[PDB]
Amino acid sequence: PLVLDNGSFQVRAGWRLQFRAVCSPFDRNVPVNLELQELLLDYSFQHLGVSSQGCVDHPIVLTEAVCNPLYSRQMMSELLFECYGIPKVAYGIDSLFSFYHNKPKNSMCSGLIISSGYQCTHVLPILEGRLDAKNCKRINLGGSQAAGYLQRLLQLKYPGHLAAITLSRMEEILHEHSYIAEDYVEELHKWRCPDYYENNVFVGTERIRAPEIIFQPSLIGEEQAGIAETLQYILDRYPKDIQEMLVQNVFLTGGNTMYPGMKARMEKELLEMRPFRSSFQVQLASNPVLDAWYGARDWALNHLDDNEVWITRKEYEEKGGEYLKE
Amino acid sequence: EGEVTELTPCGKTISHVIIGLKTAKGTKQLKLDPSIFESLQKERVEAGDVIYIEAN
Image 1 (cartoon, rainbow over the protein chains, first blue to last red):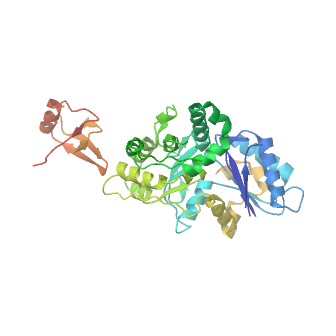
Image 2 (tube, rainbow over the protein chains, first blue to last red; image 1 turned 60 degrees about the vertical axis):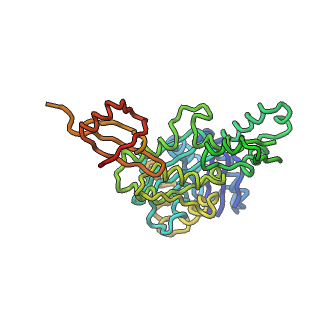
Image 3 (cartoon, rainbow over the protein chains, first blue to last red; image 1 turned 90 degrees about the vertical axis):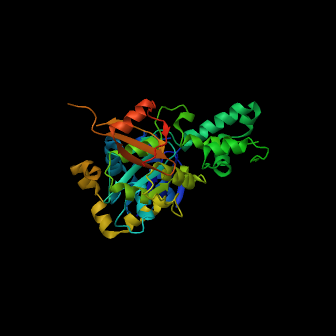
């Protein structure tokens, strides 16, 4: 069985191989190209070394973004059944797989999950084992637009430094050399002192200033409220009983969460916004980047979960996409 | 003591006033009487003001 996780910037396939989605069929986590999506799937199968021309003999899994289009699911299902003709197919969620891998017991999963993706950031609570679609929060900003904005600021810093440093190289240098500070007020105060960080590959405080756009919507010019307002408005309408588990379990996965200090800053901010009696605990898996592929490999590895979750192409064609949608 | 997020007063008069308090160590809520609410109105307390109140 092949686990296929389709992200906006990157796609990760396994049973292993992760590649860029630029051929970009997936924009704002919603795939805009079925032909390019099917081309990336066929290239992922050829890289996976399937025996048959089209991928058949193994059951396939496909990650679905939050609020995935039903028309895109129907077109991809019809073109995948008529063209690829896999023996079995199923749909899954990267946040649900990473949460199932992060939870000590795979049977029960609870707590508000924060998933930071490339073109979007989705944070939704989960209780009883089923995700609540009413409390789900989506964000159009992401690490791709953050890296592009950082390369734009560094491009406006010096005219020659823009042509000397590539956008991808500046994105990797922003991945390794930049971290999220716990106190944004203490960071600017620490940058004004004679002793400076001075990361040279000269990069100034813009390393920590560029990643601050994730927690600060007003930095990039967006009109979105923010993560604190999303947590307050999300936890305000919910009952007071689920707040203890929501604060007790907080999952952070994805490539955009690889910034250091984000767990401590999220624990300090979450502990500051939450009540004094409620205990806030943020959980970060040892492999949060591959946690989605690992959880998908486990869900596909479970026999009963593959029998109930798996949907045939012939039966899914007669029943429609509402079977996998519900 | 702390920041006041909301003021929600609840033959009408005032039965009680709901007042929130938010600090970096946590958030709590208190219901107060129209007398101390009258003290707050004399102090021109509005949403977003950090206040100090002693119970005794």
